[PDB]
Length: 149
Image 1 (cartoon, one colour):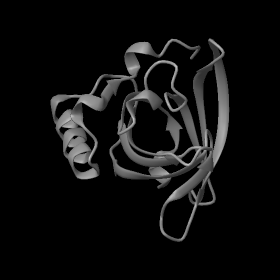
Image 2 (image 1 turned 60 degrees about the vertical axis):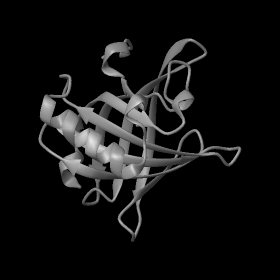
Image 3 (image 1 turned 45 degrees about the horizontal axis):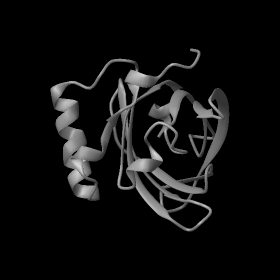
């Protein structure tokens, strides 16, 4: 998981509860950076979300557990882990349990800046099928990444 360290942007996000990741949704986030500590057992994530119609730069810490997942508190409880890592992309799975108890299953693809290639899109589709997330719920987040670098 040490391969997680560096500058990253959110390229695509897919979720079973689509309203969570559309504009205005609490889980629509725009990565900026991941810093790893202690052989990446602590993963600090820096990102932007829009809150009250303003860009809100945020940091949270993901804590690695014995089961190989990371837990972080943000808009509820999150349980996430990399599904597949390359030098220019990270495909993560995340399960969010909000404060009402609603569970949302998501796939987040982080990248260095470019849109996904055809092969990367195929990998994403295979993951969406495996996780039971509709392909019509795959959103292009890079297109609306408007907050400061």
